[PDB]
Image 1 (cartoon, rainbow, N blue to C red):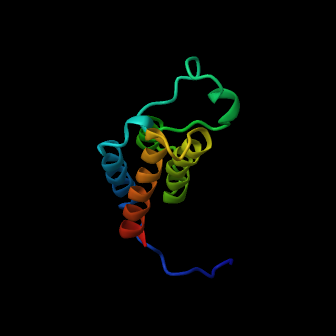
Image 2: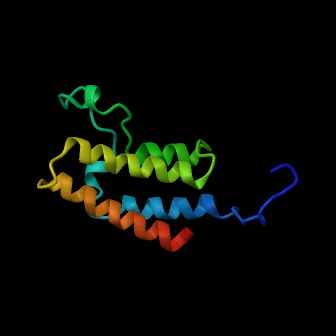
Image 3: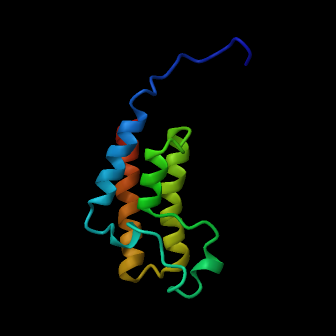
Length: 115
């Protein structure tokens, strides 16, 4: 509360460390469905159904331009990419499997780096 604070965590490396995680996600062999924004002119139903499209290139641009206020807002966009994927793609499909794989890959790096 006012004048009552928990000891100050060092957040000075967070930006660099999120950049590194994102590089590792970008270079994973199953990243291909997520590298670029879904083409809303060429994929029927996507625009109406997926209210907040997200992809790795858009996260990279937000990260590089100071549009993440803290490491939680960064995690929320990465998780949005996989939540969108599950919304639109059957579990038993190449893209559906890709999304589950990448979500697990992310959550381990996230825990190991920050928890």
